[PDB]
């Protein structure tokens, strides 16, 4: 924990809110020009944890809520998530009367304490029903996007997440009216009949310096799973798939050349860095264990 | 009259309606200001949603009132 | 001892986010204060959530707002049903008379308030989170009050476990000014450090046993012998061949992957040369 910096780190400016910049970016409205504008959604660790806990706590029923944050450039930042007092069946949720009063009161109370962020989106949980936009979510997301432009639909699946051990969070945004534009068919199948109406987004997560510092001492028995990590063995299929997509991207960039090369180089660097990190861990293990009593 | 209507995302709307006037008047003010359909709108004052059947003649609005506007949302 | 308290890995994240957000907003580090919620089952207290609280300052005294607390208590009951006020938290180091004053003021709300202390500016590897319990002793005269230290647990839900593991295994949060090599090597360094500490403790124990200053245990010594007769783990030739094969494969994967980056730099250089040097 020493021989480094302990003050405001380079992962804390993401948590800083600038009112003037947000006002300028809201007045600019760069989203209306290119409709494929937003492509990245950065969610805080706290927001994701709260969303997953609330979705799982609902049991087999469906739950819904809001999420705060802001928007910068080509990315949407989602910082906090607060639930709603909704009473939904196994398929549909309504949020009839007490949900909106809760929204207004909670936003006002949060602004009282110091929460300077505004509402940035809504989320609703599919209890084992995959991760896609239904014919009602599409309509309500279009309704929200028509007037409150900075918005995003987050879909979470609690049952599948708890059964498979991996979170299933999907960020989506709807195209406006009249916007038309051995390989698996899941690309069309896993979406509803409105597959051409909405498009997904790249979901990433971030955490603060204090978040990582406190989570470093979260538990002191994963060291065994790190020493006997067995890297380059549990994700070989991942690396082969990455190599295949990298070859496809290289072919596309070569066709274009005859700026697309930048993302291909980035993907290649990422895959190679992962492989080199795995080899480094294996070399460290070999030096630690097998180089003793020779 | 400069009654303020605020959406949760930060949009601002200014309307002009006398207190004796019906809440349908507020509804069509926001209609001709933005265009959100009448059946897809909810308005909140003082933390309590007003009903359509209450005329704002005996109402705790004496100027400076801010109305929180939200859009109905549903999921499946 | 006293009342067994069960802490979830969501309160601590709430405190850390609170501290980070207010420190960023105010520029300088500050003190944050809130309120915990949970359940009371017999002799067991469980804290599972927390919400922020508003506090004002009168010269030196810190006064917790009561009307805002009441509104928040009425509001949070709609979403969470079996949740009740349990205690209050703050961020700071050693206990302070300001904390005792705040606890005495807060005592007017619940009968047995807890006291969760978080250390955001810790300077050691000791646990930064400490659960304190303030029971009113029967000492007469001046109220000599020392909050009893509590050995909290880490009771956690299944979805909470999944989310906590997902955030713990996160690595893309940085990869900016700090090299990803540093982040990859830090985990290995910490794991090796903990293993080295454990084996150093074992070595100290066996040195003490051979010195004669401790009672001689015939079973632990033979267990240590069994452990120590297996350090060269799997030194067969097949393992060496497999290791060399893996190293060669990763070397090829690095070669094919440095070539493309060199080609991209090539393309950028030729593009720049074909505009800023080419004669139209």
Image (cartoon, rainbow, N blue to C red):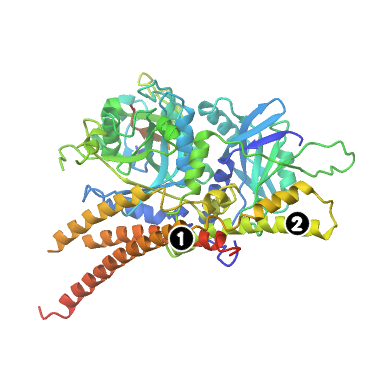
Q: Residues within 10 Å of mark 1 (few under 14, many from 20)?
A: few
- Tell me the distance, in whole angstroms, between the alpha carbons under discs 2 and 1: 33 Å
Q: Position of residue B65 (x, y in %)?
A: 42, 35
**Quadrant containing the C terminus of chain C in the rendered view:** bottom left
Judged left or right of residue A167, residue C115 is: right
Foreground residue, C124 or C250?
Answer: C250
Foreground residue, C1 or C199?
Answer: C199
Q: Residues within 10 Å of mark 2 (few under 14, many from 20)?
A: some
Foreground residue, A273 or A191?
Answer: A273
Residue position for label 1: C240
| First along the sequence among labels 2 and 1 | 2
Q: Is residue C23 shown above or below C147?
A: below
Q: Secondary structure at mark 2?
A: helix
Q: Quadrant of residue C40?
A: top right
**Quadrant containing the N terminus of chain C in the rendered view:** top right
Q: Which mark is residue C206?
A: 2
Q: Secondary structure at mark 1?
A: helix
Number of residue marks: 2
Judged left or right of residue A251, residue C105 is: right
Judged left or right of residue A54, residue C156 is: right
Q: Quadrant of residue B59?
A: top left
Mark 2 or 1: in front is 1
- Whether residue C237 is visible, yes or no, is yes
Most distant residue in the right direction = C141
Q: Position of residue A256 (x, y in %)?
A: 15, 60
């Amino acid at each position: 924990l020493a021989n480094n910096m302990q003050e405001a780190q380079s992962i804390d400016e993401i948590y800083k809110y600038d009112k003037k910049q947000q006002q300028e970016i809201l007045a600019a409205k760069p989203w209306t020009k290119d409709h494929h504008y937003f492509k990245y959604c950065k969610i805080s660790a706290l927001a994701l944890l709260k969303m997953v806990m609330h979705a799982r706590s609902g049991g087999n029923l469906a739950v819904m809520g809001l999420m705060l944050g802001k928007v910068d450039g080509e990315t949407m930042i989602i910082m906090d998530s607060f639930a709603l007092p909704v009473e939904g069946t196994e398929t549909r949720v309504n949020a009839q009367a007490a949900a909106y009063e809760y929204m207004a009161a909670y936003i006002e109370n949060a602004k009282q304490v110091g929460r300077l962020e505004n509402a940035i989106g809504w989320y609703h949980s599919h209890p084992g029903y995959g991760c896609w936009l239904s014919g009602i979510n599409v309509s309500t997301q279009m309704l929200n996007q028509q007037f409150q432009e900075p918005f995003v639909a987050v879909v979470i699946d609690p049952t599948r997440t708890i059964s498979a051990g991996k979170v299933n969070l999907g960020a989506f945004r709807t195209y406006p009216k009249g916007y038309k534009p051995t390989i698996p068919l899941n690309k069309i199948e896993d979406f509803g009949v409105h597959c051409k109406q909405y498009y997904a987004l790249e979901v990433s997560y971030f955490k603060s310096s204090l978040d990582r510092k406190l989570l470093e001492l979260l538990w002191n028995k994963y060291w065994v799973n790190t020493l006997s990590s067995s890297s380059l063995l549990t994700n070989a299929d991942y690396t082969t798939g990455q190599v295949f997509d990298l070859s496809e991207k290289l072919e596309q960039s070569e066709a274009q050349l005859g700026d697309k090369l930048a993302k291909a180089t980035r993907d290649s660097c990422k895959t190679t860095i992962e492989a080199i990190h795995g080899l480094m861990s294996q070399v460290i293990k070999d030096k630690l264990f097998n180089q003793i009593n020779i | 009259m400069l009654i303020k209507v605020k959406t949760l995302t930060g949009k601002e709307i200014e309307i002009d309606i006398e207190p004796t006037d019906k809440v349908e008047r507020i509804k069509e003010r926001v209609e001709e200001k933005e265009g959100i359909p009448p059946q897809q709108q909810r308005l909140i004052y003082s933390g309590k949603q007003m009903n359509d059947e209450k005329t704002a003649a005996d109402y705790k609005i004496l100027g400076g009132s801010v109305l929180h506007l939200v859009l109905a949302l549903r999921g499946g | 001892g006293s009342v067994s308290v069960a802490l979830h890995p969501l309160v601590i994240l709430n405190i850390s986010d609170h501290w980070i957000r207010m420190r960023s907003q105010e520029g300088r580090p500050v003190q944050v204060i809130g309120a915990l919620i949970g359940k009371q089952e017999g002799r067991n207290i469980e804290v599972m959530n927390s919400f922020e609280l508003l506090s004002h300052t009168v010269e030196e005294k810190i006064i917790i707002d009561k009307e805002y607390y009441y509104t928040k208590e009425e509001q949070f009951k709609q979403v969470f049903k079996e949740l009740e006020f349990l205690g209050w938290y703050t961020t700071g180091g050693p206990p302070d008379p300001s904390d005792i004053h705040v606890h005495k003021q807060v005592c007017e709300i619940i009968e047995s308030p807890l006291f969760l202390k978080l250390n955001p500016m810790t300077k050691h590897t000791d646990l930064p989170v400490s659960v304190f319990e303030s029971v009113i002793d029967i000492i007469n005269g001046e109220a000599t009050m020392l909050f009893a230290e509590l050995t909290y647990t880490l009771a956690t839900e299944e979805a909470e476990r999944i989310g906590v593991d997902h955030v713990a295994r996160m690595t893309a949060t940085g990869s900016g000014e700090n090299s990803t090599v540093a982040e990859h090597l830090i985990a290995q360094h910490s794991a090796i450090k903990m293993l080295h500490s454990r084996v150093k403790l074992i070595l100290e124990y066996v040195k003490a046993s051979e010195a004669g200053e401790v009672p001689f245990n015939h079973e632990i010594l033979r267990e240590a012998y069994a452990l120590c007769h297996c350090l060269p783990v799997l030194s067969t030739d097949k393992f060496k061949t497999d290791f060399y094969d893996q190293c060669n494969d990763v070397g090829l994967m690095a070669y094919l992957g440095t070539i493309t980056k060199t080609c991209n730099t090539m393309n950028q250089f030729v593009n720049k040369f074909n505009v800023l040097y080419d004669r139209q």
